[PDB]
Image (cartoon, rainbow, N blue to C red; front, side, top):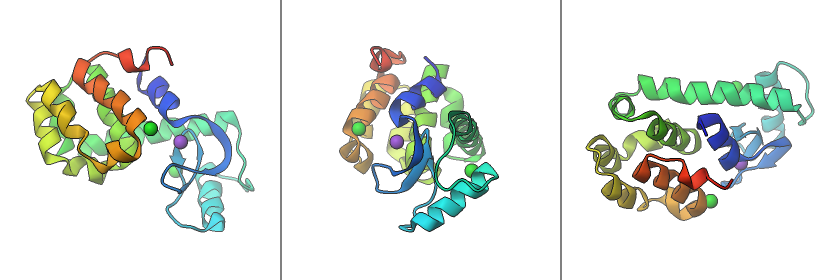
Length: 164
Ligand SMILES: [Cl-]
Ligand SMILES: [Cl-]
Ligand SMILES: [K+]
């Protein structure tokens, strides 16, 4: 298990433009194209991201390319965020992956704002942190995924991704 395998399980792999859980145009491995309700806008973003006129369909290799960029970008954002960096730096690798996962899905801004959860994590109060994290729109809207991420933070193990 690793952050790529983990997010690959949580995000799936789809080669054509589709709507994510929030109803936003996405493609590949959770590559958010835009929040715009316009398919055309989404196609325009895709073409720009990929470097060619796609007409909304990409290859697996292309999906993987965006994904790698996305994973890296999330990490990079974390390292550049004053709120997340210290937390991120305080964690073991497994937990770091859980954090990257959250940022990838929720967005850096949202995560950076979970002040209390972030503090519990940094304090290494795993169970408490886990309880705290569930008190969110995040958990409510995507509880199965949230539970996996949460268990990862609680335990420091990949048990949640075990038989996936
Ligand atoms: Cl991009
Ligand atoms: Cl879910
Ligand atoms: K998805």
